[PDB]
Image (cartoon, rainbow, N blue to C red; front, side, top):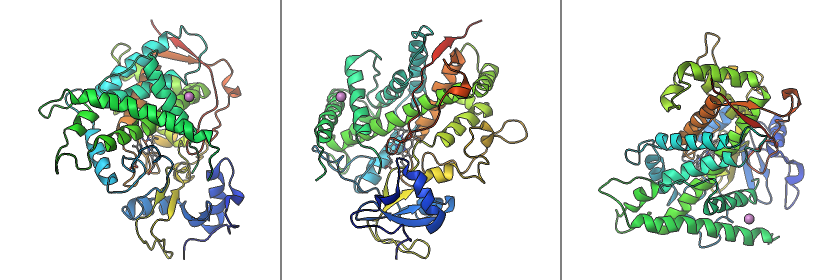
Length: 449
Ligand code: HEM
Ligand SMILES: [Sm+3]
C-alpha cells in the first residue's frame, strides 16, 4: 500500500492545490505526514516532505528514487536522450560525461572560472552603459548566464545586441515558460515549441558541425570538443550527434533560466535590504581590491558575502518542488511500498524553510549562515540544488556565477531603487516549477573615488 492520501475524485485530485502547489502539499503533509501520495490525474505520485523523508529517499535510496517521468519535450525527432528527463541507458552516461567535463578544468587551460570572469567583466560594462538610469535587469541578467554556457559549450560568447543570440534566448525562454508546473492540444502551444525547439536544435548543431572541423590531441576546449572526441566502444556509443544536442539543450535550458532568475532575485533582495548590500561591499573592499576583479579564491575569505548568497538561495526557494522524480522498480520505503514507475516529488521548500534548521525561515537573514562568533559559514538543510544522484549538474559553475557576478556588480555599483525599501514587493509568484520574483526597476549607480 502506498502512502496515505487526500482521497481522489475520478480523473483527478487537483481538487485541492493552488497556484502554489508547494503551499498545499504542505497543507497535506500536516495530516498524512512526511510521506503521502496524491493523484495528479489518474496516476499516483507520492510526496516526500520532511527533511528526513527527503534525504532518506534522495540520498539513502539513491538508485531507487532516481527517475522523472514525462513526454512532451520528446516530440520533434527528440529521442529520450540527454541529461534532464529520461532513461539511465542515456542518463547515467550523458550525466557522468557531463559532471566530469563540466569541472572547472575539464576543458583545457581556460578554466570555467576564467570564463565566468570574462562574462562578469562584460556584465559590469554593459551595466555601465545603463548610464545610471532606471532599468529592468531582467534582460542583461539573463544574458550573462546564457553566455557562460555559450562559453563552456562553443567557446564563443555573444554580444548582448547580437540578433542570433537574442534569438537563441527568445527560444529557450518561451519554451520553459510554456511548460510550467508538474488530447490536450490548445494547441498553438505545441507548434510554437516545435518552432523554438527547432531553432535551438539548429543553432547548436551549426556549432557542432564547425566544431568538427577543428580539434586536438586530447586538447579539447569545451563540451562539444570533449563529446566529439568520444569514438570509444565503436564509432558512436551513447555519444551520437543527436544525443549531444539534447544535452546542450538541457544544459542551456536548465542552466540559463535558473541562474538568471536568481541573479534578478538577488538584486531585489539587496534593494529590499540594503544593509546586506553595504556589508557585502565592506567585505568586498576589505579582501578584494577596488581594482582587480573577483576570483573564486576570495570566497573562502568572505564568510558574510557567502552567507548572503547562501541565504538568497535558501530564501527564494527557486524550485519548491524540484523536477519530477520516479522510482526505478519496486521499493519498500518505510512501512509502505512504492511500485516501479511511480512519480515522486520532493518538497525542497520544506527543507529550505525548515524552522529548526533556519529559525525564522520566512526571514531573509544572512545570519542563518553565520556563527555567533565572528562571521563564519555553516549549513545542511541547504538543498537548493537538490541532493540525489539527480542532483544539479551545474551546481559547481552555478555557485561560481552567483558569487563572481553578484560580487563584481556590487564591487562596481551602488544599487538604488525608485521606491523606499519598506514599499517594494519581493513576494514570489510560481510559474510552474520556478518561483519568479515580482517586477522591479533600478539604477546601477557607479562607484569611484
Ligand atoms: C541558480 C542555479 C541553479 C539552481 C538552483 C539549480 C537547481 C537544480 C535543481 C533543483 C535541479 C533538479 C532537481 C532534481 O532532479 O533532483 C536541477 C537540474 C539540473 N540542472 Fe540546475 N540549477 C542551477 C544551475 C544550473 C546550471 C547553470 C546548469 C548548467 C550548466 C544546470 C543544469 C542542470 C541540469 C542539466 C539538470 C538535470 C540533472 C539530471 O537530471 O540529472 N543547472 N538543477
Ligand atoms: Sm517568440
